Image (cartoon, coloured by chain):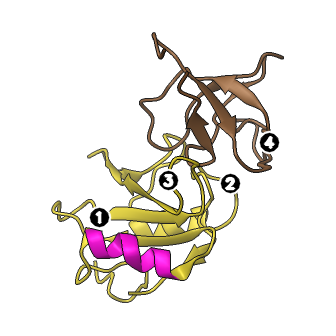
């Protein structure tokens, strides 16, 4: 797996507080657009919600 | 910049020690800093119970040094600071580019 991009999931119940950051939720999965970033890793919700997401609360599913 | 005045700043402590020292805290948001080689770029050692692969995990956000006029210290591509102390105060609350937004300082 990991052809070009990977999927990540939020371990805890994190919530947004800024337009830039993206609201998350447990058992919620997204995609990875920017893994190079050390702090936040861009994600794209199926719904179409794009914003910066945490790195520690997110982990690559690694299929 | 007499950083010895602050607690997050700690040069006498090594990186390896910084990892275990924060672990002793056992708290979410536990943040600390460590003097790096660069005379103008320490290291923000952030500890938070997270990541499933390995927990507890230690996050090290090296301060981005963008030698500008002024501006140089920053870790979020959002706002830039001319002093580390500022980055520590701003992130301590409001809303910054930290996976846990500094909220709990630690001493060496």
Q: Nearer the viewer, mark 4 or mark 1?
A: 4
Q: Quadrant of the C terminus of chain B?
A: bottom left
Q: Which residues are magenta?
A: B16-24
Q: Kindly tell me whether residue B66 is visible in this rendering.
A: yes
Q: Is residue B102 above or below residue A31?
A: below
In the picture, the disc for residue B42 is: 1
In the picture, the disc for residue A26 is: 4
> Does the residue at mark 4 contact the one at mark 1 (Cβ under 8 Å)?
no
Q: Colour of chain A?
A: brown
Q: CA distance from mark 2 to mark 1?
A: 22 Å
* Label 4 in the same subunit as label 3: no
Circle 3 residues within 10 Å: few <14, some 14–19, many ≥20: few
Q: Quadrant of residue A60?
A: top right
Q: CA distance from mark 2 to mark 3?
A: 26 Å
What type of secondary structure mainly makes up the magenta span? helix
Q: CA distance from mark 4 to mark 3?
A: 18 Å
Q: Is residue B84 above or below residue A7?
A: below
Identify the residue position indicated by label 3 in the image: B54
Identify the residue position indicated by label 2 in the image: B95
Q: CA distance from mark 3 to mark 1?
A: 25 Å
Residue occupying image coordinates x 57% and y 77%: B26
Q: Quadrant of the N terminus of chain B?
A: bottom left
Q: In the rendered structure, which disc, 2 or 3, sits on the residue that comes first in sequence?
A: 3
User: Residue B5 or B33: which is nearer the viewer?
Assistant: B33
Residue occupying image coordinates x 75% and y 21%: A45
Q: Nearer the viewer, mark 4 or mark 3?
A: 3
In the image, taking residue B37 as reference, residue B45 lies left or right, namely right
Q: Nearer the viewer, mark 3 or mark 1?
A: 3
């Amino acid at each position: 797996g990991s052809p070009e991009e990977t999927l990540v999931i939020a371990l805890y119940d994190y919530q947004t507080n800024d337009p830039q950051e993206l609201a998350l939720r447990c058992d919620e999965e997204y995609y990875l657009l920017d893994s190079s970033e050390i702090h936040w890793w861009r994600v794209q919700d199926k719904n179409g919600h794009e914003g910066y997401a945490p790195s520690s609360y997110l982990v690559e599913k690694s299929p | 910049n007499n950083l010895e005045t602050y607690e997050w700043y700690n040069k006498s402590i090594s990186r390896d020690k910084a990892e275990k020292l924060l672990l002793d805290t056992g708290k979410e948001g536990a943040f600390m800093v460590r003097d790096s080689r660069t005379p103008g770029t320490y290291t923000v050692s952030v500890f938070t119970k997270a990541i499933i692969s390995e927990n507890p995990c230690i996050k090290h956000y090296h301060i981005k040094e963008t030698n500008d006029s002024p501006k140089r210290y920053y870790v979020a591509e959002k706002y830039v600071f001319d002093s580390i102390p500022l980055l520590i105060q701003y992130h301590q609350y409001n809303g910054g580019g930290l996976v846990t937004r500094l909220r709990y300082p630690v001493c060496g």
